[PDB]
Length: 197
Length: 197
Ligand SMILES: Cc1c2c(c(O)c3c(O)cccc13)C(=O)[C@]1(O)C(=O)C(C(N)=O)=C(O)[C@@H](N(C)C)[C@@H]1C2
Ligand SMILES: Cc1c2c(c(O)c3c(O)cccc13)C(=O)[C@]1(O)C(=O)C(C(N)=O)=C(O)[C@@H](N(C)C)[C@@H]1C2
Ligand SMILES: [Mg+2]
Ligand SMILES: [Mg+2]
Picture 1 (spheres, each protein chain N blue to C red):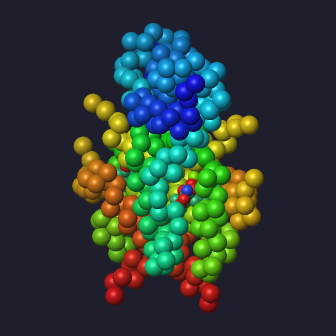
Picture 2: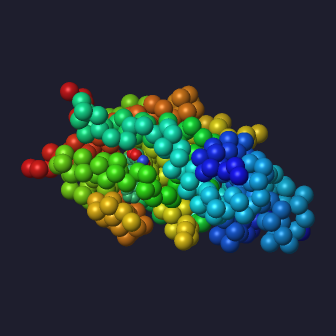
Picture 3: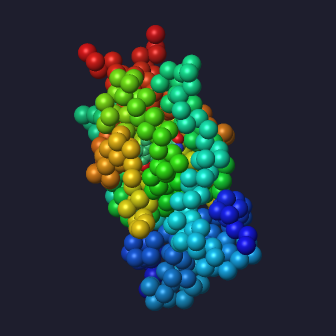
């Protein structure tokens, strides 16, 4: 035979970069792979399945700060977790739209479970931990979808502050903005814990 | 003749809901409107132009907390601005993907300019103001793209904390998560100002 699932997914990651999330189809993956539709069907049963597969495997491949390191404060962890998640979303074309709307995978259960436990052990109620992890994902993803969709935008007279505001944001493709509000999020949450009185 | 730009855009808003951002095309707008391509062309010259038009007009129509109200702290403003932006993104199918990657419009220059001035007058450096407005948009947009792409996901065994974490997030389609981390953002920034010593 031929097809192991990781080869299929690797071809799918190449295709995503070549044609983007919209033009990525099951039928096109089968072209690139050199195979019939119903042999692909056993690995990836529809487009949704395929996209969920990319979402996961992109994180398996490039999202390595999944867990607090022995020397880390929950502050450190959150920072380095979020940075790692963002570079991982930036790695692929439409990486932000690939992730959006997924839920963590079986391959991510033990670490994601751990991320929440780690936050509960830090002082946070569950809700709080859930909302903080969730929302740092949303923040990061929003940051990445915007900068990705922006530089893909080939369109063809701001006021003073707005001119600088947009200059500042086109400069680093959103880096400093990201790091700053990650930092205010983490101080925000610090104040949540200080709300033990 | 027939076509004023607002009728075209109104038809485009109906279509977006009917077919979504991917299936929305210039050629399809012309169908719905009852008109030839090159007569549409004068209002909306390509797909990008069209999408930028939706992005703006959706905010013109549904994003009404553009400015601090006489009785508002910058805290109040940011909160109510962000809430207003999010409900505005939720109003349309793919509203989050319609906004992503745009830059504020001519119709938004005087208010957006004002939002930054207002923040500078509050104590924030420009950078800070730019990063806070930018990033609250990113946060809100990420929050909305995720919940929208999620409920559109018709796919067909979590651990304990993860089971609750996801239950909590499917409950309110992300509301409480949003309000909580908006609140920690705004406390985060409060600490930025306390960093005048
Ligand atoms: C806790 C949680 C997370 C995620 C998530 O999508 C999610 C959800 O959809 C419902 C309830 C909880 C969560 C993440 O996407 C994820 O990005 C993720 O899978 C993840 C990962 N695989 O390690 C992370 O590290 C997290 N980090 C970016 C905050 C975050 C954790
Ligand atoms: C300041 C700013 C903003 C936005 C933005 O896209 C942006 C940018 O792309 C580069 C530099 C600055 C900004 C907004 O989208 C917008 O959503 C917006 O247009 C906007 C609006 N039209 O009133 C807002 O109220 C803002 N709020 C959600 C923080 C935010 C303001
Ligand atoms: Mg996720
Ligand atoms: Mg914007």
